[PDB]
Image 1 (tube, chains in turn blue, cyan):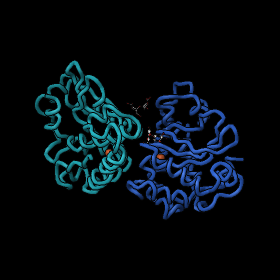
Image 2: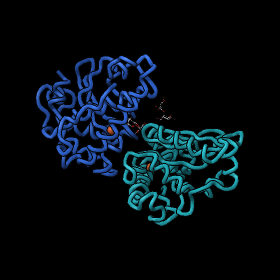
Image 3: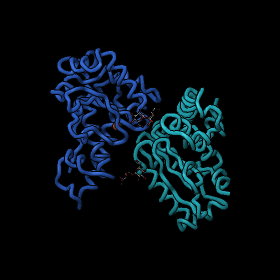
Image 4: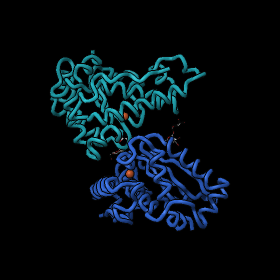
Length: 192
Length: 192
Ligand SMILES: OC[C@H]1O[C@H](O[C@H]2O[C@H](CO)[C@@H](O)[C@H](O)[C@H]2O)[C@H](O)[C@@H](O)[C@@H]1O
Ligand SMILES: OC[C@H]1O[C@H](O[C@H]2O[C@H](CO)[C@@H](O)[C@H](O)[C@H]2O)[C@H](O)[C@@H](O)[C@@H]1O
Ligand SMILES: [Fe+2]
Ligand SMILES: [Fe+2]
């Protein structure tokens, strides 16, 4: 049975960009529910003994939405940090300059993809087969984890539960907290 | 240019099922924003002089997302009332029993469709071409308004902004609020 991974930092730790209550609900309840639902769905199926990733990569319907949502949320928590934010560093900063010319252009491109990602969705920083970076949008539980040859680097959850408690309807304000939390170490580990 | 319709009731008329705060953000900001976006999109285009329903029935991409959304939300405020709730009456009560055997079986079927309607979505009570009632789920901005032979009767908004402020992650509590508010008078009008 799959389990809810612990949060990589205190429920307190992303303040004032993402609040304790958001983490309590977003991780403690939303994330957990996909874990629970998934565990309920696997018995009696060909997903009985496969790893999370194996299932997300081979399922559809209910098993997929729940499995992918677990993986996506786990990847999202890793994409934030009480010690992140600010300028990118390392391999990632250079690839960002290589693709977009500057960090600022990359940031304006991701903000634009993110605010316009209609409905419950996710905006991703991914590394392509050709080694280059790109920004791709997925809807609901969809994830580049299943795009062959594409490597997920960072993600921002845009389902409303992710920011409604702290930002109501204003995604840019949310995106602001995201940029003050971005976990460049996790980005660089995925990139390398 | 299109306009934000007024709410059919006072801002606190739906308390304690839907809070004045939710009404302020949902109707005053989200609903509004769809109107503003569509006004910002149709100038100079073919849609410029069409009615809202003509636009929804003839567009895609962003024009459709905003048009359908203004339409869906206006239908939704109408689907709630400070004087609704409790048992269905009239024509709709009888068609409900014709389809589901009883009002109680109908509630369980709608609740079920709505709690499992994944991501930003809407759950509708509809009248089909054979004259019978059914419940259908649409995603994001999609609406049965565009389905041939299908007439919208009532809708419950399941995008998280519709209930997060009041019910956080617990959709069944929000659906109990909906049942205390359902406008049978609007439903019987749509039906006849
Ligand atoms: O796990 C239950 C099902 O979830 C999805 O379907 C639900 O959500 C859809 C919108 O995302 C609705 O259109 C649909 O009516 C709901 O049943 C998934 O597509 C299904 O395969 C799952 O069984
Ligand atoms: O009007 C802008 C576009 O809105 C939609 O696309 C955005 O939201 C999608 C998810 O609903 C994302 O996948 C997409 O990347 C975003 O641009 C709509 O589907 C497009 O047709 C519109 O042009
Ligand atoms: Fe989430
Ligand atoms: Fe809404």
